[PDB]
Image (cartoon, rainbow over all chains, first blue to last red; front, side):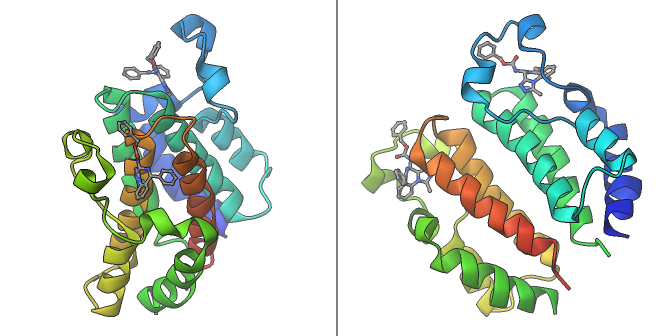
Length: 105
Length: 105
Ligand SMILES: Cc1nnc2n1-c1ccccc1C(c1ccccc1)=N[C@H]2NC(=O)OCc1ccccc1
Ligand SMILES: Cc1nnc2n1-c1ccccc1C(c1ccccc1)=N[C@H]2NC(=O)OCc1ccccc1
């Protein structure tokens, strides 16, 4: 019921979102040219991974899925500079995530 | 019911927590010697403010209170360096926040 909601309502909205594109797949540190990314960020996470996990019944509790969303956003804030656009993008998506989590069954 | 839960269960646990102390009052940029804090962080938030707001029935929806917790943690990640202790402290508290939010009525 709760994981159904996270998949059917929360992920549906965030995946579609205008600012979703950077978070749809794992950060490729080599392509992006970020040699220090995996030195700073120890637990990478992204929406593609969360989506697969929801589809394949990976999670046992809603909170596990919620923690993955949180880790995704947090990594972005920790690695990037405050003035970066990605930071505003993460904030916008996280706000919507928390709003819908408040309405979870 | 939901705001009661946020006050009685969520705030109760986080306020007591070992790592709560830096977040119990607004960041005093002058005392802490952070001249650029309010240039970078545009919406300051802290647990003291959230606690007063819960006590005084300030909030209309649980999500408003949840957004304040999120803003508090996010500010910490954006302003501080990745290796700072406060960053680990925020992560620990945020994990507990999200865990209890998953059990909200
Ligand atoms: C997700 C995520 N998390 N971080 C990043 N993405 C990301 C993932 C996939 C694609 C893009 C991005 C964007 C991005 C997103 C949107 C707009 C602009 C940028 N930015 C990436 N970070 C970056 O390029 O760091 C700059 C840097 C480089 C070297 C050293 C220090 C700092
Ligand atoms: C909350 C919160 N958010 N940021 C900070 N606190 C905070 C609030 C109240 C009290 C302490 C702290 C601690 C803290 C907390 C715990 C342990 C260590 C530190 N650190 C503060 N930041 C800081 O000193 O920046 C270093 C800096 C200075 C100048 C320039 C650049 C960077």
